Image (spheres, coloured by chain):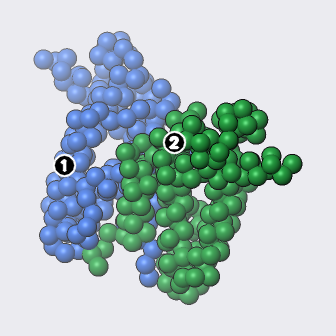
Chain colours: A green, B blue
Amino acid sequence: RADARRNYDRIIEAAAAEVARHGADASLEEIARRAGVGSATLHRHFPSRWGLLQAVFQERVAQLCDEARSLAAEHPPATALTRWLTSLAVFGAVTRGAARSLLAALDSRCEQLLTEAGADLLARAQEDGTVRDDVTALELLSLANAVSLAAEHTPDAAHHATRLMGIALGGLGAP
Amino acid sequence: ADARRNYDRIIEAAAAEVARHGADASLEEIARRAGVGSATLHRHFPSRWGLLQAVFQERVAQLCDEARSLAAEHPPATALTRWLTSLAVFGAVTRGAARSLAALDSRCEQLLTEAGADLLARAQEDGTVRDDVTALELLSLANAVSLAAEHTPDAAHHATRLMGIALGGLGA
């Protein structure tokens, strides 16, 4: 039971890092190699590619929600919000490419958790008057999601999403 | 050629209909507005898919023309934002309708890029828009908004609103 779970966690950790770092070019051989498991041990914990990607999604969403709390503790509210929304767009951009090559969408609990995290960050930044009070959490989440969709088929998906979020969140106005 | 006039009238009518109705666009309304019969329309355009592609061409031409009228009628930053809003709406409604029956061709994508680059360069030159952004980035941002708004009710409104937020940014 210890060896099994130690192996579960190592696989999910390796899978999430591989997706994050390689996107559409994510490699299952590399995941198995980096977790130090064999094909049969991998297939035992995750009989389907669906199952493994869903578990990667759940793990990354848990991390993103933790990241929102870390960012809020460590940076002014507007900075926490922009950094977090940028992370979210990058996650969507590289994770879609991975999901497309390896097979794809977030489940309802994951969308709910991200929505809560984003709403909490936006509210804190609007409350201290550093972020415009006329936008909604749904709107900003839709923008991050849309940027993910726009970036996922690009050769440099993480950089592309970063670029677009830089514009969407900073605006066009000359500094 | 009288037939070429008909072709032109069909395409202009088809473009306007999809723009206002997307997936619910009416062939009968297109033919009527074009002043041609059901059979004529069908002869020029065998498939709905083939008509949609010609619609994309026509709207791209119109968008390039729009870049000029905007630049003449509004300060460079305003011309840029309005044009990018138009592009987002086009993607949300018209390109989005292609799902009911896909994407712009490469020549058309490049034409839009060139028109965007021109508006961007003028707004950078007059110091009202940040010097570090590119036409590719802004067209990609328009694409993102189009993906966010397509297949939703009130798509044109939602595209307009999201593009507006994105170009304004979070500040103040």
Q: Are marks 1 and 2 on the same chain?
A: no
Q: Is residue B89 visible?
A: no
Chain containing the residue with disc 2: A
Chain containing the residue with disc 1: B
Is residue A9 rendered to the left or right of residue B156? right
Specify few, some or many for label 2: CA neighbours under 10 Å numbering under 14, 14-19, or 20 or more: many
Quick one: A117 or A119, which is closer to the camera?
A117
> Which residue position is annotated with label 1?
B114
| Amino acid type at mark 2 | Ala
Q: Residue at x 19, y 17 (%)?
A: B3
Quick one: A142 or B85, which is closer to the camera?
A142
Is residue B68 rendered to the left or right of residue B89? left
Q: Residue at x 40, y 38 (%)?
A: B95
Q: Which mark is residue A26?
A: 2
The quarter of the displayed image where residue A65 is located: bottom right
Q: In the image, is residue B142 above or below residue B111?
A: below
